[PDB]
């Protein structure tokens, strides 16, 4: 109910469904809506964004089913097949999805400026949906500049997935702090435990990255994510250990309100107050 704080980026999926529909990539434990909702209230956050989990591909049935289960409380982003009709996009936005995630990371580099993607890029544009990116920082500036012309919001995952043990002048992060984003570029500060480093190194870099990122994009463009249930890091990370890392960044009260509410509240339209 009360819009106290918003968690952007999170996944849900049932072990019984991952066993009944037969999947094998990264499905073992169960991440039901209830658990996530519990972990949310348990740490403050009242609203969240369900992002489509990679191992489910275009099947957004569970995400869609969980959005209706708790109306208004969640928004979530999906993954769409190459050619999709506006009809289904509208019906999804009506359900609460406000963006699409291409999600490459460990996938073959797509040519967004190409013609085999435009058919979809136009569909999401007419709906106002943003496009979520997830790939090495090295490729981010190229994917961003490709979606740049389409005039739509671009959300970058996990600091841009740079290398914690490489500095801010990294091959991809550098262009990021100098990118030409007409305020249409968002960057998510989440899952620092993915920066290919030690929990103490990623944390040191996450600290520097934030200050540099906000200095170029602004607080109204940075939002915090839990990345729950933290896939491939379940043993090391939990919702609480993720918040604790947030508290560790040492963000002033102002930025925290932007990273935990204001920003995400705008992009996903959580117009509640």
Image (spheres, grey):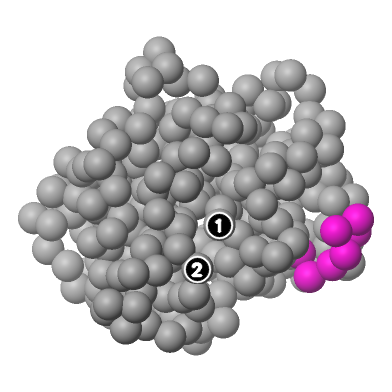
For the point 50% across and 68% down, the residue is 29
Categorize mark 1 by other alpha carbons within 10 Å: few (<14), some (14-19), many (20+).
many
In the rendered image, residue 189, in percent from the top left (x then y), is placed at 66, 47
Number of marks present in the image shown: 2
In the rendered image, residue 170, in percent from the top left (x then y), is placed at 82, 66
In the rendered image, residue 43, in percent from the top left (x then y), is placed at 61, 32
Residue at the spot of label 2: 29
Frontmost of labels 1 and 2 is 2
Whether residue 257 sits left or right of residue 62 in the image: it is right
Image mark for residue 213: none
| Residue nearest the viewer, comparing 41 with 133 | 41
- Residue 167, placed above or below residue 206: below
Whether residue 17 is visible, yes or no, is: yes
For the point 22% across and 42% down, the residue is 68
Q: Find the magenta span and give its range.
A: 195-201
Determine the secondary structure under disc 2: loop
Q: In which quarter of the image is the C terminus?
A: top left
For the point 74% across and 19% down, the residue is 253
For the point 36% across and 38% down, the residue is 74
Find the residue positioned furthest to the left: 87
Residue at the spot of label 1: 229
Whether residue 73 sits left or right of residue 133 in the image: it is left
Q: Is 134 inside the magenta-drawn segment?
A: no
User: Which label's residue is closer to the chain start, 1 or 2?
Assistant: 2
Whether residue 205 sits left or right of residue 238 in the image: it is right
Q: Distance from label 1 to label 2 (Cα)?
A: 10 Å
Whether residue 10 sits left or right of residue 253 in the image: it is left
| Residue nearest the viewer, comparing 179 with 267 | 267
Marks 1 and 2: CB-CB under 8 Å? yes
In the rendered image, residue 165, in percent from the top left (x then y), is placed at 89, 67
């Amino acid at each position: 109910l009360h819009l106290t704080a918003i968690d952007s980026h999170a996944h849900v999926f049932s072990r019984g469904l991952n066993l009944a529909s037969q999947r094998r990539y990264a499905p073992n434990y169960d991440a039901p809506l209830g658990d996530y909702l519990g972990q949310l209230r348990a740490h403050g956050f009242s609203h969240g964004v369900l992002v489509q989990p990679s191992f489910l591909g275009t099947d957004n049935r569970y995400l869609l089913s969980a959005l209706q289960t708790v109306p208004g409380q969640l928004r979530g982003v999906v993954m769409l097949e190459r050619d999709v009709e506006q009809a289904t996009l509208a019906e999804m936005a009506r359900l609460g999805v406000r963006g699409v995630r291409l999600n490459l990371m460990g996938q073959d580099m797509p040519d967004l400026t190409g013609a085999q993607w435009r058919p979809l890029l136009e569909r999401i544009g007419e709906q106002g949906w943003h496009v979520e990116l997830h790939r090495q920082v090295a490729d981010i500036p190229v994917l961003v500049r490709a979606l740049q012309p389409y005039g739509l919001d671009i959300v970058i995952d996990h600091f841009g997935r740079p290398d914690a043990r490489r500095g801010l002048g990294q091959p991809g992060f550098a262009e990021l702090l100098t990118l030409s984003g007409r305020g249409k570029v968002w960057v998510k500060v989440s899952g620092i435990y993915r920066l290919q480093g030690s929990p103490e190194e990623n944390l040191a870099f996450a600290r520097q990255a934030l200050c540099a990122l906000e200095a170029h994009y602004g607080a109204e463009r940075l939002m915090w994510g839990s990345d729950w249930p933290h896939t491939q890091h379940e043993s090391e990370v939990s919702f609480g250990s993720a918040v604790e890392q947030f508290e560790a960044l040492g963000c002033s009260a102002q930025l925290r309100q932007a990273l935990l509410l204001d920003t995400a509240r705008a992009l996903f339209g959580f117009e509640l107050e």
